[PDB]
Length: 129
Ligand SMILES: [Cl-]
Ligand SMILES: [Cl-]
Ligand SMILES: [Cl-]
Ligand code: NA
Image (cartoon, rainbow, N blue to C red):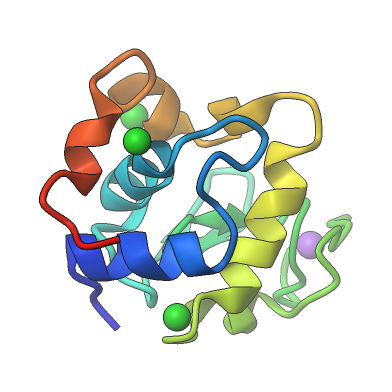
């Protein structure tokens, strides 16, 4: 599923991400825009053999099991394919664990490079929330 900007903002808010660990909703929408272009089915392989999955590009070396990343830890206790669903629940639940692990949203490279320190509330402007 390819979400619209306001559609995703509303789903993210319903799932408890607004101000989660102090990160306003626009941070999460901006991160999803640049990680996946709002596409729940996005995958990208990394040089170390791990793969990033879904709307927030969650990595198989640490967070989910895809059966082909040796030494991975599956800290969200899910198969990575669950992160590609049109229902974002599994991605959101896993992201809550990632963002709580000490490094905040810096875990998402595109957030660090393209969202951090910008006017992120522009990503939710005009949306009925
Ligand atoms: Cl915001
Ligand atoms: Cl959803
Ligand atoms: Cl980047
Ligand atoms: Na893993």
